[PDB]
Image (cartoon, coloured by chain):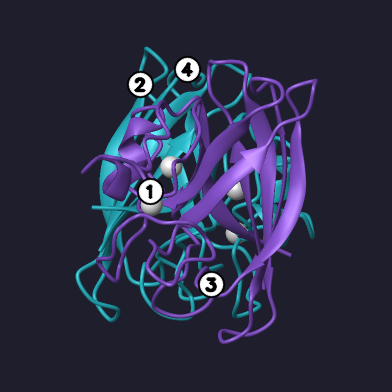
Chain colours: A cyan, B purple
Amino acid sequence: VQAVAVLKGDAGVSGVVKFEQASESEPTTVSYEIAGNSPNAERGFHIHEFGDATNGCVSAGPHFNPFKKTHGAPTDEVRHVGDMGNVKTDENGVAKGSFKDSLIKLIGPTSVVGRSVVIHAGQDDLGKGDTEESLKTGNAGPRPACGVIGLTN
Amino acid sequence: VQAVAVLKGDAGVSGVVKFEQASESEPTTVSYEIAGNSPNAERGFHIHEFGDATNGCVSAGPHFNPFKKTHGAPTDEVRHVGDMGNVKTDENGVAKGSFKDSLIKLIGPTSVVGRSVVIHAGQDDLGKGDTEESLKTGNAGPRPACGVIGLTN
Ligand SMILES: [Cu+2]
Ligand SMILES: [Cu+2]
Ligand SMILES: [Zn+2]
Ligand SMILES: [Zn+2]
């Protein structure tokens, strides 16, 4: 199964995030190309609950969290399903990369098809900050771009 | 269950299409508000197969047609799952309305969550035309706007 999200916004950030998953129990491969970010930085990157684009990136809602866990790093076992950590940006503001994830799925009752991807303006502190906010959002800040995740082939 | 598609493009047409379905066997209520169309007209309106926005409205693919039927009117038994007929536009170019449909679902293996809605620049001939093309697209013409269908609440 394949899916894709086209990230758009008004802040100069835009990109494309691709998903592929062979079967429900197998990892999903997530790959991304994102332009217009701050250079030489780390930027929070998550699946949010709703595929709702009626109000910018606000209407995407919170991090996708069906299991009611705190916010964490992708390699933490306690994390939101949608937590994809930080993406690294180069000297030109480009984030490009890929990873595998075993919580993110395109199949079954936690499928992210129809949800959203958000790229943030700040760094995700991976749930390790001082704040109650760290356990909710990682303090990753504003949502310069987002896109609904759709089926493709 | 609720879903929504935000229709966008570069042709002056834009809008929002909402979906609600209580359970898989019951009708889906589809409501829409679309601006910027030709006035006093009828414009084709369909669910297309893919929620892929990487190439304008082209990458949405063809009408959603899992049962491999010909294109028809919503009230035809032989139609594509995605066939929503024409929407009527007023003297200001606005289409606003709602309807129930029993093939379109937000639940189950034919769910349209993660697919696309397209509003066309021309009238859908409902499969009644003189063409092979009528039985594929209803001759509804260009795709001035589209949006991926996402989960909301
Ligand atoms: Cu986020
Ligand atoms: Cu169409
Ligand atoms: Zn999170
Ligand atoms: Zn059709």
Mark 2 vs ligand 1: CB below 8 Å: no
> Residue A125, position in %: x, y?
59, 48
Q: CA distance from mark 3 to mark 4?
A: 37 Å
Residue bearing the label numbered 4: A36
Mark 2 and mark 1: span between their CA atoms?
55 Å
| Residue type at the position of mark 2 | Asp
Q: Earlier in the sequence, mark 3 or mark 1?
A: 3
Give the residue pinned by disc 2.
A90
Disc 3 CB within 8 Å of nearest ligand 4 atom? no
User: CB under 8 Å between callouts 3 and 1?
Assistant: no
User: Which amino acid type is marked by label 4?
Assistant: Gly
Q: Are there few (<14), some (14-19), or many (20+) residues within 10 Å of tag 1?
A: some
Residue drawn at (24%, 66%) of the image: B68
Kind of residue at disc 1: Lys
Query: How busy is the neighbourhood of tag 3: few (under 14 within 10 Å), some, or many (20 plus)?
Result: many
A16 over A2 or under it: above or below: above
